[PDB]
Amino acid sequence: ANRATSAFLDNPHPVGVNYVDEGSRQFVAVAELLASKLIDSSRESDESNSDVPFVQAYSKFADDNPRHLRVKTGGKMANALTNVIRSYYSINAPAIVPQVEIDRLASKATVSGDMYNSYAIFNSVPIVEVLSPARTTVSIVGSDRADVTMLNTGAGAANITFNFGQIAETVILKGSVPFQLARLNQPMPAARFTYKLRPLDGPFIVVLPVGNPLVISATAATRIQVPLAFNKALVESGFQTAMNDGLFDIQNVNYYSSFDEFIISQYHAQDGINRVSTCVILGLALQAYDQMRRALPV
Amino acid sequence: ANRATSAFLDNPHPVGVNYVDEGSRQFVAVAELLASKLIDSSRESDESNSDVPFVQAYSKFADDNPRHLRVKTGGKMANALTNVIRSYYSINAPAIVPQVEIDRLASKATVSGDMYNSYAIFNSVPIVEVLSPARTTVSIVGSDRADVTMLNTGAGAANITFNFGQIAETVILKGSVPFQLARLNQPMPAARFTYKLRPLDGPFIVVLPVGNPLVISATAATRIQVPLAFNKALVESGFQTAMNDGLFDIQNVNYYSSFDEFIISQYHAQDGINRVSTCVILGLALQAYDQMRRALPV
Amino acid sequence: ANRATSAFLDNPHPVGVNYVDEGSRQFVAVAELLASKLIDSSRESDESNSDVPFVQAYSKFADDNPRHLRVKTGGKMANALTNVIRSYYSINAPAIVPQVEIDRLASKATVSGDMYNSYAIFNSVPIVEVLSPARTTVSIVGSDRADVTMLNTGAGAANITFNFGQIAETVILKGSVPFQLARLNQPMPAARFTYKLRPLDGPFIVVLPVGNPLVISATAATRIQVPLAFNKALVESGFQTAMNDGLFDIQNVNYYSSFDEFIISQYHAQDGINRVSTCVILGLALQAYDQMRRALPV
Amino acid sequence: ANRATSAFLDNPHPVGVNYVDEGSRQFVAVAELLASKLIDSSRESDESNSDVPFVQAYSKFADDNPRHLRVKTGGKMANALTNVIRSYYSINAPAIVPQVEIDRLASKATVSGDMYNSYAIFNSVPIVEVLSPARTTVSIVGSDRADVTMLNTGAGAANITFNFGQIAETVILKGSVPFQLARLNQPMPAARFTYKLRPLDGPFIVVLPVGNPLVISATAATRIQVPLAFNKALVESGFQTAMNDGLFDIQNVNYYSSFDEFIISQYHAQDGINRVSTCVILGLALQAYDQMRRALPVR
Amino acid sequence: KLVGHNYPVYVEPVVNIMNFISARFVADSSYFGYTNEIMIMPNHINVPVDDRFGFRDSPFCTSLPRTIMGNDVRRISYNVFSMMEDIDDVISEGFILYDAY
Amino acid sequence: HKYHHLLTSQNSPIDWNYHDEEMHKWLDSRKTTNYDAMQKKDGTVIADIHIPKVFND
Amino acid sequence: MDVLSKGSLKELLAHLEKTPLEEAISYRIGTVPYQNVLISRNEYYNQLYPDTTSLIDGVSREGQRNVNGLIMSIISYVVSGSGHYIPNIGFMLLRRSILDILTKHDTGLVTNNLNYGIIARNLTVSKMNCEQRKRMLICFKLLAYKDGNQNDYEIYLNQNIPLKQIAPNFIPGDMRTVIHNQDQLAIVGIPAYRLTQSTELSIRDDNAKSYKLGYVDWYNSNSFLRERSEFNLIRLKDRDTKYGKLNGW
């Protein structure tokens, strides 16, 4: 008997515990709000035929007026946002930003750092384990759409067990050819192309006939509570920008292809609820980072 | 030895050479700005009971007033935008639009920016070559997420060479089972699930054991300089519309699934630094084409 | 016999023949003057807590007002300066910048394009030919200081002929141990550590004792006419930056470590007198390129 | 297989981590600006019949009026600059200057603390490793111009691998006699005197014929971001003075012949991007030290 | 407070009317008596002009040309033009002034 | 013990059969050159009693 | 709450000189640390929120009856507001001030064998913030100069670069250094942002927020000393004077 698991779900590293309180949460909300005004100031500059709208936006974000002989960096808030993002990813990252600096930057705009007033859908499909008997090959490829390739070289039909965890809300399975799937201690129905199932129900048994390989595609949806200012497209771009800039370059940590995989992998840890709150705050910080760095490249 | 390359990296066709000067670049920016005001005006007119915002937006865009009987072609701006998109794609395109007409249309508005003010992240993964010994078989499938399936049927472990080029910033490798990867002429580490690499580090060797096949999933991120008004969501949808409307049906040209694949393929070629400049201009033109067409379907 | 020749004197490539008229020389002189103003304005603007000195100095150089959302690259003058550097290095360069543009840029300042107002001393050591008899080994290493190591494995004393060319003014030879040197058909003096020689005198003969290897250290000084604004420190920095930025990456050309080696190598060619005039103009163009790139990094 | 390395690239000691904030960067820039004015004021007063320009310049720099029968040390700014230089060089050096004193001195003049305004070119050639077969011998000598002497005592031709790292931008190889050099898995070209290389291209293979030794001279250029006020001639002169004055005398630190070698060595170590930032600030401090000490020499 | 105000959802119609008029002032400048570019040329250079209205020696062009008689037309910003010294030689041929109203 | 099992299984990061084979060839090569070096310095009989050929493995 | 409000080296050191050691210890048994627990956080979740108990929380915890435990309780009081449960120490030691325990040989406590590595590990330093780390480094510096272990303190800082960057700069025997220091060591204070009456998920964050909201109530209560209004009512001994300096410094 062999077992297989998703690659992105292996060994989630611990996340940081700093910059989670109310003042730090409001700093991230202010940074997101002010960085958004920076991007919109470009369109205002085009319409107004002048750089005054951009100068006003940068002055509020950086406490200093822009210069022509200096490369625009963002000043204290840019430095604070960058260092705070580093601390969120790993517990080994230092917490360099002082509290006093965080409170001063959090007073720039009026926001509430409530990160539980909305939700988002995360599409990473968790396959905790797939148990197959001898003379059966199982390969799991993919993270957003997981394709499971199954081959039965044995004499008779085999029973393969799926375990999708206890966190995902729904999972939809679509097979290359019609197949049979049922819960444990349940009878099997007629072969169908598509199955919709709740992972909380229990481990699922799929009957593998002997012959050509059977491939099953898995798509899952998970609901995680996020602030109302959350935007998945901006968060995903911020994740790639931060990884390129080396903000995640620190020893004894894991690397993920997308923010979708990062948050779901942390949610499936030993105590994944503790890390979901920090990961969401990292998402808002990354959304602020993508806007800030696209307006002020460096 | 066997060589396997990504399909979208093969033979990038030459890109058009006209309408790339400062005046022509200003015209694309103005067309994008005016088209954005057109689609925003159309939504407000639908929301409200009166059609004033659309009438003004179309008059500025088309240099004539809308009529209930005649069709809304978009004016001479729509005609010029359509033809320059054709010219940008291939060098064999006609490119017969007068330059005086381009300058006239570029004087409608003024833009406070250029085509190098910001950056964008492109997710296509470049696999220039995968080199394998006599007995192993390698198949590469996928552009957004490359999936490399390698199988060893020889006596002992083989070494597979991966070449990711020198342009991409970071490449993340995930495997169905743990595997070993190291740089050329370097000792191999213990087996892990995920690797993070810098393609400029050099060709990478992967140890392939004899037995069940190994599938490696690769995700890459590339940074290309773009104007601040760039939006990948609008560009990608504009790319599909241009293909469906047959703006790219020219002889001896290559066809790509997404604009992300098109820009990476041109970048991974000799004189690719000069080619991305025209591809970025084409991308912004596709953004204007999307917004203009969704407001004025024909 | 055996022949040893300094490495940097081997096959100098022909220099360009364009942009050598009186108008082009004024353009190079104008560019150097306005490039120096850019550096000083950046300093003055920094010390005055204002950007007006830099904005005005950049406006003269680039013929365009600086903008906060636009990339500053030097404008038209930066492009023409880059292209004339390419033309000067090799005769295979395209030489694309027109003459009308050269005169337009040369009218910004009233500076005479005189390339023979002053002189400069260059320290490259020209060793055209070292002739040694059989069963002796001679090796030449170094350009600024030439270390000639000769070993005599024969039975008796050996005679080695040094040819320093007819271009350098003075050459000073220092040996590890006292040695004997004399002209052709002249008596040999007592062994001395140091010799001062005029290369026009003729080939010089050294006597090699059979005992231990002898090393001769050669230092030379050559006088070349240059404009008054010539600064070797700025010229050397400009040479490396231009090579780094790929302004010399044209096929079928030779590459040199420093500018002193470049000008001396072409001085020793058949048409060296005509080549030095073009090389000096490139030196002033390289001096302007260094200052302008330091004030406006890209 | 034997390995050969550059002497200056070994074991870079950690550099200081204090006095690298924005307020501290302003102090170094102010000190450099005020030190230059001190030199020009002394020249102006020497050429004139009055000492007023020097009196005003020294009073601003030292916070006390110059006096006869006094040593004219430089005052508190001189002490702060000297101790700040010690901190940057080594992590074992104490940090004794209060931040309040540094902030007070930084308010004397108005200048930006930009350490990334411009760029400078450093000429030290990094030869990370030279890998040679068993029959051959290789000797690397030099820092600004690296000469590698290559001798083949074996029966046939040997292949030696040159690795210049990934930091340097261009490397120019010039040989005593024409030789052959090409990248890995590339055909060997015709024997030619000079080669231009991009160190990022990969390890380079050079064919060593059996016979007379072959010497290859290597020169490299590297670009490091520096403030606009950076002056290489003044930095190098200040580097030698501080070493002579004992400012770099501390336990467990490597020593370098020039500032070019110092900055390149830290660049090639791990966290080299973070280390060069501190080295640049130390370079500007050494520029101020040279001007200030040449204007006011002390025993 | 003046520059950090956020527009309410129920903006009064007067604010929208003033915003509309201000936008048209910046965008369509020719309707109000100002432009951004002018051309100054000698009288012996003949440039095609807008001849629809029938004016004698019409000072109106459909668009200011980038080439005249196959030759590129000089473009000078108002800032550089102010500090220029040999303005008599420059005006001997045409030039386009921009970067000003 | 989980790592111990991995290093002695078929999916080990170390290919043992290659290394044990290479160790055998290296040792036999050393035996030949050590004996031949002695056979030059002293007689065949002296070398035989000092480096026997009957004690391979 | 009073200890966490000190914002400067002068105020923090002055407070430690006035307060006795009994404030650092607690007489409530509490629970044990390093235990995985399920706590109830109903404003956010219906299930039980996992967390881990530590010595840095503001709740009293059982501590070891040795010198190591006594020092951990003192640093915990400084960086968290509450100490541990170490009873029967003795009235001779409990009367003396916290500063005297830290930097005076007359007390009789022997602290030379203490290792800063395990103390930082036990007083979990990967979970502290910048202000908490600075206060701990102050206590380490005071102890090191008490037993003449300045060299060991420097080597420990050189091993951990982030600690060196934020390490306060003051000599424990000199009062001029305390005056010149401008580090911000306040963990509670009047907030510029909007502080609400809401719970936080972690044990450390919830307890810290309780101290923060408690300080606001105390700041606006009658126990606070408003210097601008009643500076003439304080006694002359406790009035703020620049000549004032710590005893023995």
Image (tube, coloured by chain):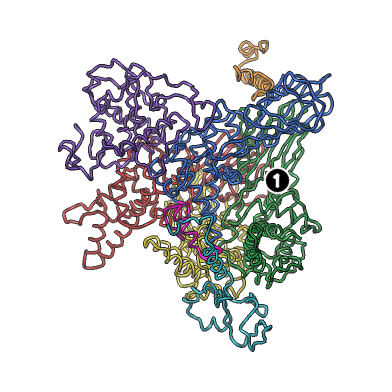
Chain colours: A blue, B green, C yellow, D red, E cyan, F orange, G purple
The answer to whether residue D108 is above or below residue C16 is: above
The answer to whether residue E58 is above or below residue G63 is: below
Residue A59 falls within the magenta-colored stretch: yes
Q: Which residue is identified by label 1?
A: D187
Q: Chain of mark 1?
A: D
Q: Secondary structure at mark 1?
A: loop
Q: Locate the N terminus of chain E and report the quarter of the image it occupies.
A: bottom left
**Mark 1 crowd level (few <14, some 14–19, many ≥20, 10 Å Cα):** few
The answer to whether residue D259 is above or below residue A123 is: below
Q: Residue at x 49, y 45 (%)?
A: A29
**Looking at the rendering, which quadrant does residue B88 occupy?**
bottom right
Judge whether residue C263 can be spotted in this image. no
Residue E84 falls within the magenta-colored stretch: no
**Looking at the rendering, which quadrant does residue B52 occupy?**
bottom right
C102 and E76: which is toward the camera: E76
The count of marks equals: 1
B66 and G204: which is toward the camera: B66
What's drawn in magenta, residue-wise? A45-74
Q: Is residue A275 left or right of residue B292?
A: left
Q: Residue at x 76, y 25 (%)?
A: A181
The kind of residue tagged 1 is: Pro
Q: Is residue D6 left or right of residue A209?
A: left
C79 and D18: which is toward the camera: D18
